[PDB]
Amino acid sequence: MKIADYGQLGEYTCDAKCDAEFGEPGNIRHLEGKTYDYRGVFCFNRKNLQEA
Amino acid sequence: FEASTIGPAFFTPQVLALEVDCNIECASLLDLYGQIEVSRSTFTY
């Protein structure tokens, strides 16, 4: 997971007002990755390898 | 590392204990001849 944002909630308001507003809530994101592979191959000649 | 791509230094040949010699020496007639012993550079008879 990752917390992208927290958002804004609440504000200072005039006392005479009798209600309040809705803010803009934050955002959360789901992320994922991957794993990679390394490979190779090599070959020999038996007699040459044995006599070297 | 194929043997056909690297230098000869990586392979040491087997050392054999034999030698080839075709030379000859003919038989001698020396023992037929008469033998004489001297101790000076000249002689008389």
Image (cartoon, helix red, strand yellow):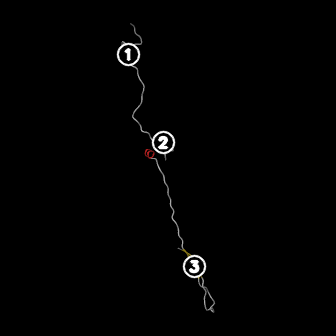
- In three-dimensional space, the C-alpha distance between marks 1 and 3, rounded to whole angstroms, equals 126 Å
Q: Secondary structure at mark 1?
A: helix
Total marks shown come to: 3
- Tag of residue A26: 3
- In three-dimensional space, the C-alpha distance between marks 3 and 2, rounded to whole angstroms, equals 73 Å
Q: What residue do we see at 57% from left, 79% from top? A: A26
Nearer-the-camera pick, B36 or A47? A47
Residue identifier under label 2: B9
| Crowd band around label 1 with a 10 angstrom C-alpha radius: few (<14), some (14–19), many (20+) | few
Nearer-the-camera pick, A15 or A42? A42
Say left or right for B14 vs A7: left
User: From the viewer's perspective, is residue A2 above or below residue A14?
Assistant: above
Q: Amino acid at mark 1?
A: Leu
| Crowd band around label 3 with a 10 angstrom C-alpha radius: few (<14), some (14–19), many (20+) | few
Nearer-the-camera pick, B35 or B33? B33
Q: Secondary structure at mark 2?
A: helix
Tags 3 and 2 in contact by the CB under 8 Å rule?
no
Q: Amino acid at mark 2?
A: Ala
User: From the viewer's perspective, is residue B10 above or below residue A4?
Assistant: above
Q: Quadrant of residue B12?
A: top left
Are labels 1 and 2 assigned to the same chain?
yes
Residue identifier under label 1: B30
Chain ID at mark 1: B
Residue B30, given in percent of the width and then of the height, sits at 38, 16
Residue A20, given in percent of the width and then of the height, sits at 60, 88
- In three-dimensional space, the C-alpha distance between marks 1 and 2, rounded to whole angstroms, equals 54 Å
